[PDB]
Image (cartoon, rainbow, N blue to C red):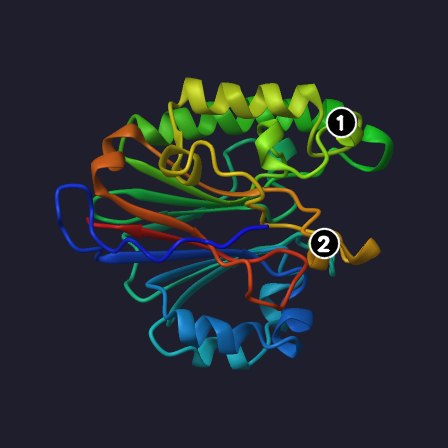
Amino acid sequence: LYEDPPDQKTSPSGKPATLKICSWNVDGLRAWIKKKGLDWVKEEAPDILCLQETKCSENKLPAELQELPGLSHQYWSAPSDKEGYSGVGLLSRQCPLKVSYGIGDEEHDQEGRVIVAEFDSFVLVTAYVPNAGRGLVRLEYRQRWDEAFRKFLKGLASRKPLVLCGDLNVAHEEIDLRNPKGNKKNAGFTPQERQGFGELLQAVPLADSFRHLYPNTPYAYTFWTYMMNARSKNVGWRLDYFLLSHSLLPALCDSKIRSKALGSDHCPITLYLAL
Ligand SMILES: [Mg+2]
């Protein structure tokens, strides 16, 4: 149902891509490593790799990671005492000017969900947004997270062009999932989460890189439940995004969905910028 087109490696002005960013919700760093996740990273060779749902504390990291050639500057965030839950990682070829953790709000900074890495010409944010939960029991909290995260990113974008990547835990529009009808009362497709995502795009402001380039392309998903043969049937959701400041749109080469890369219940996404 979906074939990601070939990589467009030049900006519209003809400038070659100089920066390749890869984002991937790994569904547990060790589970991902066993399913050959690293091998794929080596073939992809990104300049920056953002990982979500590492489920790993910084003191219990797999030794195979620090070894990664060309991704030697590594930063991790996990819940302090809570093992096997949430966790994000940012691995970079080049050293960032500054790395920070969280969104500057105590209530929202306890689950190791955000890493901010400032570079010379942009700020990179990687996030694992909180799921609205089974039966939507964490939806009110999710709406408070949405508001604090929008405010935080608006503050960052005012200082430097912003690239936000990661698992944002929302399929924005009906085109973003296989079954919009059956999912309006489920986490990831509630009107509340959809509205929050629309407000993030308008308030920062940010542009959805994949949708900017491919506005009518259906069946392009980044997550399929491990249950009910969803990935073989392409019953998926586009939960993973690259969101860019409008000033970075002339640097945008391509925004890829690496549908065939195995290793997780999510597939990786890749961004090419001519910075
Ligand atoms: Mg998971």
Check disc 2 and report the residue beneath it: 233
- Residue 16: % across, % down: 17, 55
Label 2 near ligand 1 (CB < 8 Å):
no
Q: Seen in the image, is 64 located left or right of residue 253?
A: right
Q: Is residue 39 left or right of residue 6?
A: right
Q: Give the label on residue 181, or none.
A: 1
User: Does the image show residue 137?
Assistant: no
Callout 2 amino acid:
Lys
Front position among marks 1 and 2: 2
Residue 198 x, y percent position in the rendering: 52, 21
- Quadrant of the displayed image that contains ligand 1: bottom right
Determine which quarter of the picture holds residue 158: top left
Residue 217, can we see it? yes
Is residue 229 positioned above or below 213 on the image?
below
Q: Residue at x 69, y 51 (%)?
A: 224
Asked whether 238 or 132 is in front, the reply is 238
Residue 151 in the image: x percent, y percent?
47, 23
Q: Residues within 10 Å of mark 1 (few under 14, many from 20)?
A: few
Q: Is residue 44 above or below residue 50?
A: below
Q: Residue at x 75, y 25 (%)?
A: 184
Residue 23 got which mark? Answer: none
- From this view, report whether residue 33 is shown above or below residue 115: below
Q: Is mark 1 within 8 Å of ligand 1?
A: no
Q: Nearer the viewer, residue 216 or 56?
A: 216
The residue sitting at the right extreme is 135
Going by the picture, which residue comes out furthest to the front? Answer: 1
SS at mark 1 in the image: helix
**What type is the residue that disc 1 sits on?**
Lys
Callout 2 secondary element: helix
